Length: 149
Length: 151
Image (cartoon, rainbow over all chains, first blue to last red; front, top):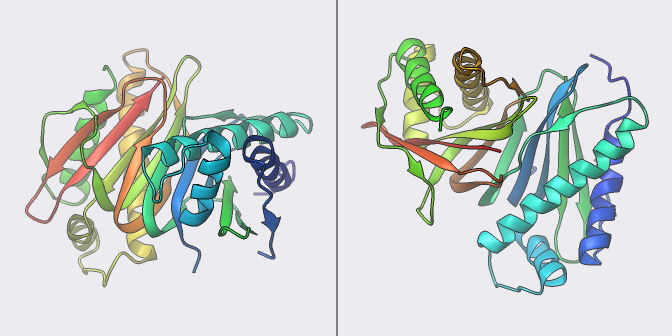
């Protein structure tokens, strides 16, 4: 079913904003196999639609965000890193919610879930268009997946 | 804690009726520092007027393949797109059943869309303000666990 608004752009802008704001780090948007090491996933429910969003990061990239965002700097994944990915997922979703409210595209957010595992893969099971948008940095890559019915 | 039994009963009833497979439930408990790993997980968010939260079902590969063989009559090669589709439908059916039971107790919520994660030995960590409850399960084909958090 066609969306009543282009819901991808606000998630892309919010992710770049949140990482520049909270971690002084800039991601380069890329041209849109897909795997990562730590992912933040959140469900969304609205009147005219329901869906989910995920942000997947390479370990190297998550660690650099950790170093710049909190000062904690472990050599590998841990609870600290997952808490950070969880809060980033909430902030990105919140930023996109505020932008999409301008176009009458309203939704409420659930609570985030964080998955950790070298090279795990993600498959949104929504009956709608699945959009995958990759990002790169000198520390590793990330990708957002979004699907609304 | 009113949401614990409806979710636990729903996973056992979905697998017993739809895949003719019996899971052995261990006593649910507040998750702490305990190891909770699996190979394929279904994750879904829930939003109600006065509550919100998330649920995950994690399966060992052996158990997922056994469920798939029972629900289709042909054992899949590995955790292919057909296995992830099945984990998504199981996540929807378990949440749908819990939602119907909790609605009779005045606990109302709507579900988001399920997301399925694949990765040998991956871990799941819910981030919500309420208590994270883990419900372990066992079978000779492998283990599974439900994690749930409502705020």
